[PDB]
Length: 69
Length: 118
Image (cartoon, rainbow over all chains, first blue to last red; front, top):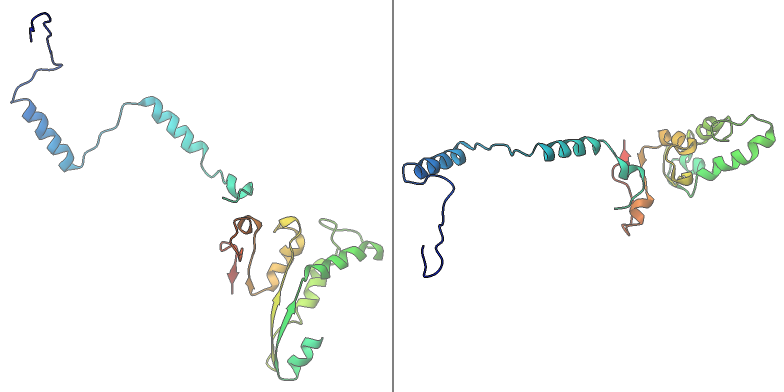
């Protein structure tokens, strides 16, 4: 879009067409239908969460300090 | 004794004991003066026998029945102190009240995860 004083190019990130976007849409219809879910890539949150789950297990602190709750 | 009499007369009786813990606390107060080596937490060496020799005669029989409700104080809220621990075995239905519930305003404060019945 070359306006009177400013030309701006609204580029995109990946090749676009119809043969492709339809492939992506079929893949998404496929993933939802097959009930397929992939894992995130956060290898940090995974370790943090695992250490937090293991440290909090069988802790029984509330039965021991008489917190009324 | 007064209860046993009505029992043996053929009747059926209700016996309410207001605090049976004092019966053993009075034994503990006197034990050391009777010259008897102390035991687990200062309790008399004959705690379990003193407690059984009483609670074995408060029972129903073929000639009559006694129905009894007994309050049992547990010192310092420690349900493992020898005195409640040795009393638990002598009751059919045990209802365990707790301060952590009574402090919620929930009365009666029965602790449903510790009460039981034969």
